[PDB]
Amino acid sequence: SKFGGECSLKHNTCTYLKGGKNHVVNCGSAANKKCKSDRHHCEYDEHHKRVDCQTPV
Ligand SMILES: [Zn+2]
Ligand SMILES: [Zn+2]
Ligand SMILES: [Zn+2]
Image 1 (cartoon, helix red, strand yellow):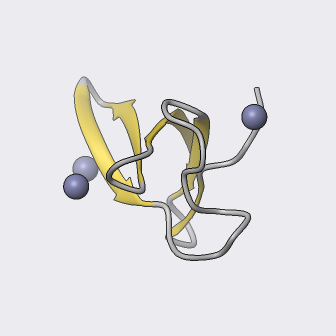
Image 2 (image 1 turned 30 degrees about the vertical axis):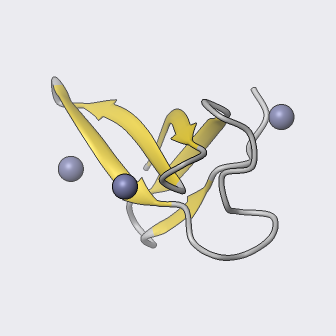
């Protein structure tokens, strides 16, 4: 189960909506996972606690 959202450049986080609430998760440090473009689409994989903040739409 993956959840899509928008990343914050300043915070290096992925923001997403789930269950009527806002959530925020750390993008991480990999060069291909950190938030590099403000509000870029990002994905949070709940099963494996992995986040990718460079996933194109
Ligand atoms: Zn922050
Ligand atoms: Zn949450
Ligand atoms: Zn892009």
